[PDB]
Image (cartoon, rainbow over all chains, first blue to last red; front, side, top):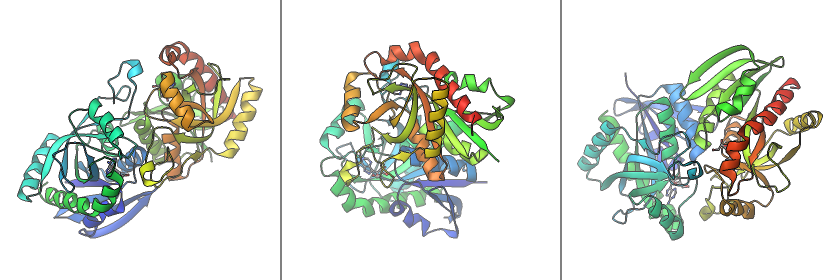
Length: 230
Length: 230
Ligand SMILES: Nc1ncnc2c([C@@H]3O[C@H](CO)[C@@H](O)[C@H]3O)n[nH]c12
Ligand SMILES: Nc1ncnc2c([C@@H]3O[C@H](CO)[C@@H](O)[C@H]3O)n[nH]c12
């Protein structure tokens, strides 16, 4: 009837939710770790994907192909590009695009992979649902464009390059768009529910280390509450 | 006993080999097209992956997970970084690395994905074998480092950035390293056998259009001959 896939890159980003599962089983294929079980009376498969585009694509492709999920939720951290955001704030995806893909030589839009869409769209019913969830959890949050690349944005120079190219980008991280592209290829609805760990600036690396735990808590709290309503 | 996977991005890059198969069947999963059959008395599954890192990862992950290949060969075109190379020259991978992955903020080597290897290694027995093949086919060829990214290198500026970062890089293209990373995760031996379609410079886009057919012919001729010896 209903199966919910949850993907995060790092152990620290999936451990809270994993420890809340009942009926837990662990499965391993390639470097991907899957934890099947029940969360808030819902079937879920939590996936630790590894970092970056390819690890995310691999993980999402097995998750879909082995567990046939009805929806996929991507959690984890991200660097804030919107100056009004603070560490710990929840980030909800509305569209997602690559900020490091340049095939403009062929006439494609900057960020667009040849023969793919310029952007990928989160499921609108999921955006609406998690929007209700964050408010009732009284967790500061924001919905917006999230951009992905295979680089850690830890300098103002990198940050300005992205801001100039995607003025409306709200946050930046490494897997969301890869997961979204994979979901597009299999036509599976998705939504990203991450949290700010840093401001993607010259202190980003230090901030990331300082707030990794905080971000995992707010994003996990939101994901758990969202799952309970699906 | 022996199953050979062959991956290329574009229809034009896989059509020659596809039309040489006997026992042909076509299978479709997501946007991936698979053609199973026999080539030079060898079982093979030819895969049209689509362009870029994520499309390549998705395609390689199903190919491995659905067909259990013993070896994987990546074919297609690439831009030459070694000035001695000419369009149509065959390119054989020795290691492969991403030229656009920057997680140096955490202390990783430029081009290295967090918690992955700096590079991925082609199967040495495959390198040796295809080296014999290109000579006996009397096709100009070269073995070396190939670098990948989610961008088309069509300007001297982009080209210099790569050359400075990877002085020994021989060629650049979009999927090889993603395929290699996927093969690393499943521990499947691989080798890249592509051909020069352009010089990755200000004429790269035009050169690509002009020599796409030539590159498909030399790379396909080499792949077909290699398969016959495996
Ligand atoms: N400022 C930033 N830039 C890029 N990625 C991240 C991240 C996320 O945390 C990991 C950083 O390597 C990775 O999974 C990515 O998605 N947090 N902050 C980031
Ligand atoms: N100079 C160049 N830069 C990047 N990719 C390519 C290619 C390859 O051809 C496609 C160009 O979009 C893609 O599959 C890529 O792997 N040929 N020449 C290239």
